[PDB]
Image 1: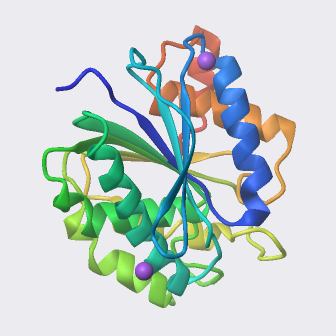
Image 2 (image 1 turned 90 degrees about the vertical axis):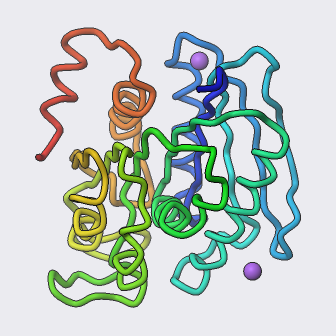
Length: 250
Ligand code: NA
Ligand code: NA
């Protein structure tokens, strides 16, 4: 197992961009370690623009991968999963890491999922250890508990491609309306049909307000606290750990 293990982060559509950027800034400030930040933007023809960089001795760089076409809907998500694989392959051709962690915000969680089910096997020496998704709409904009969107049909159909040794955290709020931008709780909850019994551990966590596009301070602090505790596996103060533990729903 290599010394570098990057945390690769994939955001959602532009409505949820402010929250994403706020999360990264705050995650950098709250983590005692300096994590270097490299940003890739995949263009609509598949070429890549780069911003920032990885320090040569940083064991845990943050790599943001987003897309010029970051719009909603299955047609776009199917392309973003190909673009993610394009960027991922460019990264494994530059840097030697054989383990990584993934953060997917909003549609980013669906993009990551589809990539993991279908495309990660193309870099067979590189393994994912942990995935956290934040308010990812596994059943798109549906408020149904029984109807399956085309999006969810594709994620469920390929769920057996997921890596069996993966640990997955899915953060959801309790908001069950669509007014923009927000995803319904009933759609985020379809995550468990994809993950349970396909991966080593699946953990649902509630953060109130996490389903809304427009963030606020108190919700971002909780989210950064969880990313640190569960995605980064950082040792946390005892009362913080215990309180985050009580946010787990299963
Ligand atoms: Na830091
Ligand atoms: Na394409």
